[PDB]
Image (tube, coloured by chain):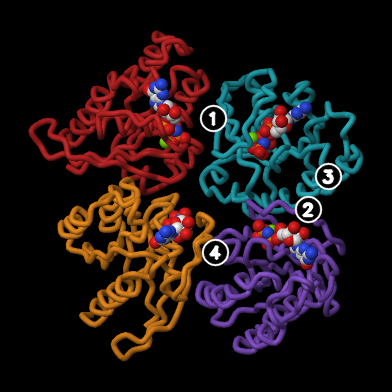
Chain colours: A cyan, B purple, C red, D orange
Amino acid sequence: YLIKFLALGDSGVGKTSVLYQYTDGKFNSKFITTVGIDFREKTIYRNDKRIKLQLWDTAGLERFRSLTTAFFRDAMGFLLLFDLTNEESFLNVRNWISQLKTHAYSENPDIVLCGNKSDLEDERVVAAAEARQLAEHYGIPYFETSAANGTNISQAIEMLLDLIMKRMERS
Amino acid sequence: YLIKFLALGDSGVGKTSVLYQYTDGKFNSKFITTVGIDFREKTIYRNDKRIKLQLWDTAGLERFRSLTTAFFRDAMGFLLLFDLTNEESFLNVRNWISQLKTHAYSENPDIVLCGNKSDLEDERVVAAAEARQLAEHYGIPYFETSAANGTNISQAIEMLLDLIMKRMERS
Amino acid sequence: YLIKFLALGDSGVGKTSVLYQYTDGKFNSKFITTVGIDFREKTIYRNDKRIKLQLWDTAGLERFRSLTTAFFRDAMGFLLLFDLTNEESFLNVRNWISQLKTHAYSENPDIVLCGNKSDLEDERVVAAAEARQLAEHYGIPYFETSAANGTNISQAIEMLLDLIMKRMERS
Amino acid sequence: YLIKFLALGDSGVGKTSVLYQYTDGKFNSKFITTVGIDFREKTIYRNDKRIKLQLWDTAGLERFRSLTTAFFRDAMGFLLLFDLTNEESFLNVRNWISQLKTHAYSENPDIVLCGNKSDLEDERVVAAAEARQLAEHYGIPYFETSAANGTNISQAIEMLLDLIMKRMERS
Ligand SMILES: Nc1nc2c(ncn2[C@@H]2O[C@H](COP(=O)(O)OP(=O)(O)NP(=O)(O)O)[C@@H](O)[C@H]2O)c(=O)[nH]1
Ligand SMILES: Nc1nc2c(ncn2[C@@H]2O[C@H](COP(=O)(O)OP(=O)(O)NP(=O)(O)O)[C@@H](O)[C@H]2O)c(=O)[nH]1
Ligand SMILES: Nc1nc2c(ncn2[C@@H]2O[C@H](COP(=O)(O)OP(=O)(O)NP(=O)(O)O)[C@@H](O)[C@H]2O)c(=O)[nH]1
Ligand SMILES: Nc1nc2c(ncn2[C@@H]2O[C@H](COP(=O)(O)OP(=O)(O)NP(=O)(O)O)[C@@H](O)[C@H]2O)c(=O)[nH]1
Ligand SMILES: [Mg+2]
Ligand SMILES: [Mg+2]
Ligand SMILES: [Mg+2]
Ligand SMILES: [Mg+2]
């Protein structure tokens, strides 16, 4: 009931800003383009249970992440993000979901897709339906998040917790 | 009938621009000198068959590529490029073809050499015969490509597909 | 009686400046933000014995340190530092002490926490009690060090030497 | 009778300029501070034999070199350089020779120490005797080299060839 999952996606998505909105309920706009392999942890109570939630952050400038073979290997669920203000990030989601399924333990591992930076209404480039459709072909939940607003952040992470808690219970 | 091969060579050759000309039939002149380990995938029909072609790109600033021991190890053919406007790139091809043969699975693995940036007629430095000769000593196909024009791009990749499809069939 | 330990913590703490104050008894204010994996060595006489002390320095821009699986794996004690003039460094100590216990050999390995840059009285941000309290919850020694002054440097390293010498003797 | 050795030392020593003086008998003053893991090869005739000499270059900004566990592991001799115009480089030689002996195959592996940049007479900082003394305590050959002049370059590499050829013959 230590629960570990991994946040991943492209550089600029906002997976550092997103974990901090959840862990600490506020928004640091300052963030070095991550070089290392950090994590924030925090105790949650969901289904009247003990959850030491361990939120592992990754460097956006590699898919060598999930080649960690311990950090990725030890993780139980994945939180794939993209930026709703660059298409490139969104288009890679297929390649991400793909490489997860292959290099992961289970054939179908527990994933939640977030389209971040939703507050940037004026720079939106990914259309919501197309996103929802991509969520359909894979049958994984989708949330339009903002680490600036907090919109759907808690929902999104709580879903991933609920998914793997189900997986844990099914066993 | 998922087919994986790896594009490699020196930094500036144009192996990112070349995969995008093939995948998407156009030319992005913008490309950050690759830091990560990306790939584009795409479904092709060659010999009335299902081809999920997986085009793996590498960072030009290492031969630590092919030390990937999974990414290189899992790949079935190699697409070695050089720039026809710097000799250094061309001269390394021997050292590349060399280190492939050694660190690869088969004694003779399936390779296609491309001399890229052929549109840069005014800055050409490698002479075509010398290139063809180098292709001779190793008995691997050679194409003078441009990611700007698309010239010989499709031909070149289709050849590499045809080679490993032959290898697959021979087994 | 070659003794190896590893200095680690965040970028800017002063673990390069601290090893040099100890090895060489003076202060180089010049220090490139470490890119490699250096060490200083030096022969010491503690409990009337031969000590080839090997002081391994790490790059502050990773927890991929302690994933070294030889450099970290071969080390016998750890010297965790933080800067008393940025809270972030101090707050990570928990996450450091945590990840050490997990990825290390022994359940409880030999650690000494240093709060560096104590000379920067005017920019002090971590309160001494809170630091001492953090040392309490884990039961590991704590020193307020300066690589500029030398204050508590020798004490701190000599303690870590004494701890693992005890561990060696107990075996 | 493929012979592999590895050139290593600190960033700025001149181990890229030195291999090129040997391979090609001239001096490129232009050299990006190496990021990757290159090698030059060349066929030599020493003791009336076939030598495919493989000269592996390393990035100066790590001792993670010799952690390559294939590139270092596959190498048969080592060519340690330092700059005669910075003491730091020279002082590390002990730590280099040390870490070689430990992480290498044989207890005493085949090493040749070069003090490079000897042409920079006006900026010389390491005194020749002190260098020769350091060579004495370890009993490995020493040459004062210049990649600018070619002075002692061929001698130095030919010695390392002769050493490991002896080791090969003794077996
Ligand atoms: N306005 C706004 N900016 C955001 C949002 N999420 C992230 N950012 C901003 O996007 C930039 C990078 O986000 P960051 O938190 O570094 O994301 P990351 O995906 O962890 N970066 P990397 O992949 O390089 O490690 C910063 O400028 C950050 O403030 C968001 O929802 N809204
Ligand atoms: N004119 C022209 N420019 C080209 C061609 N191919 C690549 N380029 C240009 O060459 C530069 C580098 O191309 P790029 O694809 O990044 O090369 P790379 O070898 O993939 N780089 P890296 O190894 O770092 O991944 C870019 O400015 C790109 O437009 C070509 O056929 N013609
Ligand atoms: N005033 C003061 N400056 C210090 C002290 N210790 C380190 N510094 C300064 O802190 C800066 C970085 O210190 P350094 O030793 O390089 O830090 P590091 O923890 O080794 N960094 P990295 O993790 O990037 O290798 C340098 O400017 C150095 O002078 C100290 O005790 N007092
Ligand atoms: N005058 C002079 N300059 C030299 C000599 N050897 C190398 N240099 C110069 O020193 C600089 C760096 O040398 P280089 O060969 O790149 O060394 P390196 O050790 O491979 N560097 P890295 O560790 O970053 O890979 C360049 O300006 C090069 O021209 C020499 O004998 N004399
Ligand atoms: Mg980040
Ligand atoms: Mg590229
Ligand atoms: Mg440092
Ligand atoms: Mg170099």
- Can you identify the residue that label 3 sits on? A87
**Label 1 – label 2 distance at C-alpha:** 44 Å
Q: Position of residue C153 (x, y in %)?
A: 28, 24
Query: Which of B168/C29 is in front?
Result: C29
User: Can residue C108 be seen?
Assistant: no
**Label 4 – label 2 distance at C-alpha:** 24 Å
Which residue is drawn at the image coordinates 40% and 45% (left, top)?
C37
Q: Contact, CB < 8 Å: mark 3 with mark 1?
A: no
Residues at marks 1 and 2 on the same chain = no
| Marking on residue B63 | 4
Q: Position of residue A12 (x, y in %)?
A: 71, 37
Query: Which of A156/D133 is in front?
Result: D133
Q: If you read the primary sequence from the N terminus, does the residue marked by circle 4 or circle 2 appear first?
A: 2
Marks 3, 4: nearer the viewer: 4
Q: Which amino acid does the dot numbered 3 rest on?
A: Glu
| Marking on residue A2 | 1
Q: Which amino acid does the dot numbered 4 rest on?
A: Arg
* Few, some or many residues within 10 Å of mark 2 (<14, 14–19, 20+): few
Residue reaching furthest to the left: C48
